[PDB]
Image (cartoon, rainbow, N blue to C red):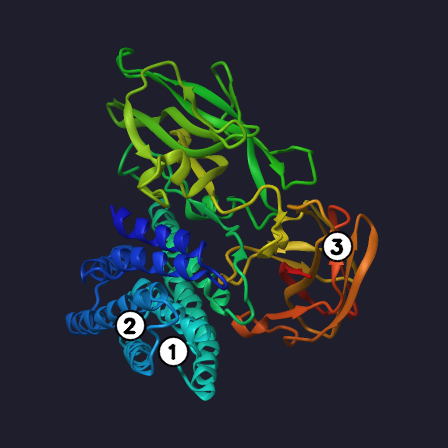
Amino acid sequence: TTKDVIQKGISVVGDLLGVVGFPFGGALVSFYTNFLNTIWPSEDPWKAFMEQVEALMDQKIADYAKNKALAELQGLQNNVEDYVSALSSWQKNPVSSRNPHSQGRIRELFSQAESHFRNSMPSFAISGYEVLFLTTYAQAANTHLFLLKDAQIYGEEWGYEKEDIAEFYKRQLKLTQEYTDHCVKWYNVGLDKLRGSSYESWVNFNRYRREMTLTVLDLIALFPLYDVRLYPKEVKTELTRDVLTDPIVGVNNLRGYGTTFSNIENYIRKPHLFDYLHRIQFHTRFQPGYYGNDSFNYWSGNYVSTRPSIGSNDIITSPFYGNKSSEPVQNLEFNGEKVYRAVANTNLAVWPSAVYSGVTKVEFSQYNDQTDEASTQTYDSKRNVGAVSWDSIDQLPPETTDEPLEKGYSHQLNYVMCFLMQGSRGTIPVLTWTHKSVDFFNMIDSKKITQLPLVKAYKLQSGASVVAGPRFTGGDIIQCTENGSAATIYVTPDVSYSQKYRARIHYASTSQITFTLSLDGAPFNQYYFDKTINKGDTLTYNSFNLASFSTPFELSGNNLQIGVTGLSAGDKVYIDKIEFIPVN
């Protein structure tokens, strides 16, 4: 269920990934048309976003609050549509038909929409309904900010006063912070409200966490890239966060046997450097049926192997998960394959006073971007397979239903982990996924501003570690507690010639610090950076600073090392991303 809103959520983020930073006019208009068809066609999507959280929370919005929200939204739709048609005409029409009279038409259309947004926002955040309005607020907030940046692109062409464009920009800055912070605060409120002790508690908890990531968290991660002044070129970026699909189970009610909340949540993958699915070792066991004829084999346990980020080749192999095989082991290898789908079969045996159920078959859809070919790999228990009951596509829809799945998919398989039920009753598999936007090669684009998340590093040092992200950066971050090296990340230059770059860093620090950059062990850039937080502060939007290094440089190597100094006992530095700006 709710796949509709999930698809819309996924698609918008996927489309925005193409118009982030300073977009070219044609691209901006194209975006806007899909945007209007997806998010702003009628009241249906908005109604579905409210129902979505109501379902996750098992609570309802007071009818009056629901109706007012929908009323505001009808009005905002007209404002957006009227605006887009005018913008579309403006781009299309030559720099001749631009008379003072048409300029005033577009200026007032724009002023109306922007103003209507600021006025309406509070309606999506009424006291007591903050969490339930989250996806609605997130989508409305996004529209407001995306709309705002247009004033910095076309402001002068439209004949706006210098004062007007500037007023819009300050307003954009303030709202980027507020909207981001509002979303994280209420996101967390909702998350804590769902923490329980039962297996059923964890499924709900995790479903909320995944759905809020796809519709809210992924979106707010893009907000900063709408600043066309800081990002005067197109931006190459990616989302590095993990999402866990619902557990694969044969029965709807496990009658108390489900793995406890703590035995799941405390054991899922913790903040780690980015990696990719390399190999899976399937363990099978025999489940006897009370009458023999109803027996079946099932997936009892597993081993998983991942390969690190580019720059390192040593394979990481997981501890054993679940139960050892009673049957012959099955191994599937994925080196250079992207698993974009997983479809599973389950089966059950009804005993006089017990029910036994397990995953009997798993078909993986893979795509090889090198040899531009899709294919499948499957796990088969070999005995009494039953029927398909679980499809990843229901939880992780494609970015586009236009192209074939091997092209339009939104996520790939990263991890597999088997949990044991209570009372030796069976196995529960849990799958972890990563976003499609992740570039394996860590490629530095010669025409765009490239954002490199630090989690893409292949080596941490001097006691640097991966820490849970503040929920608004699209992934995790690096924590530095000691003076010295911190991370080594492998970089792939896209051009052969001596292209020069400027580097920018997105960080948070308890003290004034010095960042040093080295290529293949040789220092090339060193600079001074401001303190952004006090010891013990929690990380919100304003905790981070984006600062440039003075001198330009060439990519005369691949191994980028970031070093930190100037820390005192108790000081902490958090690194989110390193950016590259193509310069002449």
Viewer-proximal residue among 456 and 281: 456
Q: Is residue 34 above or below residue 386?
A: below
In which image quadrant can residue 47 be found?
A: bottom left
Q: Quadrant of the N terminus?
A: top left
Looking at the rendered structure, the number of numbered marks drawn on it comes to 3
The percent coordinates of residue 93 (x first, y second) are 33, 66
Read off the residue under disc 1. Answer: 158
On the rendered image, what quadrant is the C terminus found in?
A: bottom right
Q: Residue at x 51, y 30 (%)?
A: 337
Q: Which residue is mark 2?
A: 124
Q: Is residue 305 visible in the rendered structure shown here? A: yes
What is the crowding at mark 2: few (fewer than 14 residues within 10 Å), some, or many (at least 20)? Answer: many
Would you say residue 117 is visible in this rendering?
A: no
Mark 3 and mark 1: span between their CA atoms? 39 Å
Q: Which residue is mark 3?
A: 554
Name which residue lies at 24% across and 70% down: 82
For numbered disc 2, what is the local secondary structure? helix
Task: Tell me: residue 241, above or below residue 552.
Answer: above
Pick the residue in front: 156 or 51: 156
In the picture, residue 517 is in which quadrant?
A: bottom right
Q: Amino acid at mark 3?
A: Glu
From mark 2 to mark 3, how far is it between C-alphas?
A: 48 Å
Using the image as rendered, state which of residue 495 and residue 396 is in the foreground: 495
Most extreme residue toward the front, as rendered?
96
